View 1: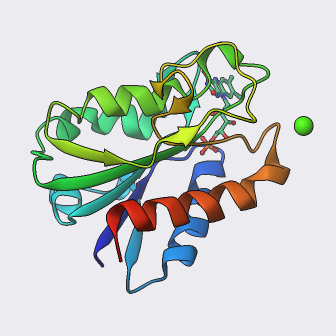
View 2: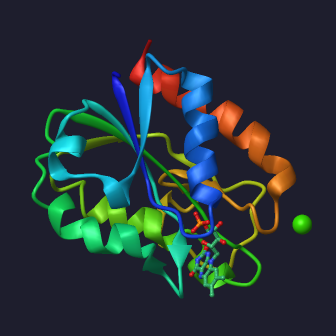
View 3: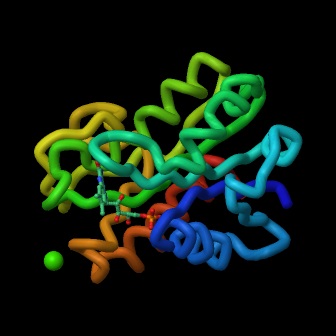
Length: 169
Ligand SMILES: Cc1cc2nc3c(=O)[nH]c(=O)nc-3n(C[C@H](O)[C@H](O)[C@H](O)COP(=O)(O)O)c2cc1C
Ligand SMILES: [Ca+2]
């Protein structure tokens, strides 16, 4: 219950990643939530937060998330450790590949969120992305279940390892 996984999902992908993630961390470690059925209180509740957001319709944010953003910007993230994950399509929307991860970064970083979990952009092949920490790493875990589902298992296995460390446990 140290970690609170909050996801948005429209066709189920991010919802599954969240669940693989919690499996890997374990239950007494983290609880998963559908941001759509979540509240401010529900988010402020945890100290370590994992936020999952898939990018929709040309750089936009999954609507459950889009609509929660205002509440999101009311939360003081100062004193909190966050990580970010999401889903994207690097071949049909290569020019907005996981931009949503970037939008949720901007809408939380100034708020004092201590972000963790940058992921190497090695192995992906998008044309552009607004969710990059540096131009060799996304700001979070980018999962492409549409084009690279075969790499989804390992990406999560390794990324969760990576965050477990950065967070310490
Ligand atoms: C019409 C349409 C627009 C989309 N636009 C984007 C986009 O701008 N960025 C991106 O990387 N993925 C884009 N995607 C792909 C989704 O983010 C991807 O399918 C993701 O796995 C969906 O996760 P969800 O099931 O959790 O919503 C789009 C998908 C569709 C069908
Ligand atoms: Ca493929």
